Length: 178
Ligand SMILES: [Zn+2]
Image (cartoon, rainbow, N blue to C red; front, side, top):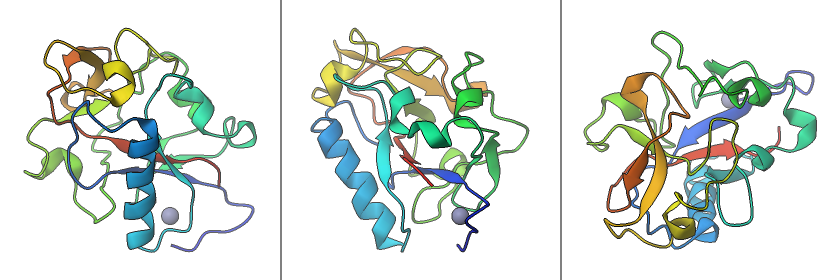
């Protein structure tokens, strides 16, 4: 990684281990993206790609970087043309053979560290928070509670599934601004 000023990019990178609903909160989830990112030398601002009590997944990326700046993976490969494109309501269709990588470089969708290939997002297809399904703002992992998740094997990044919070799923980290 070396990128150019007139060449903006935002990385969607995965946390190194699957996590249940009991994420200690977004403050706790946010801190893990931070640690892991700088453990591998990444100079950006990483926030947990989730919808919480006081925020929508949409509002993680600063306005100036929402309309054009491409969303790439840890390998710089293209995921989404832009953030608006992602949150336009098509539930982020993963293009043919696109792959997401964890900070330590594992291909999340094909590595045994992630038995369950779903992503925790707690949002609707337009990146808005769902207070009835975001594991009580990622504080609980009670099987009775549920969080919005997407099945990477269903080809989407924002599929809609109220999933039991005891589940250890993938958690993503979006660089908040290039
Ligand atoms: Zn890069």
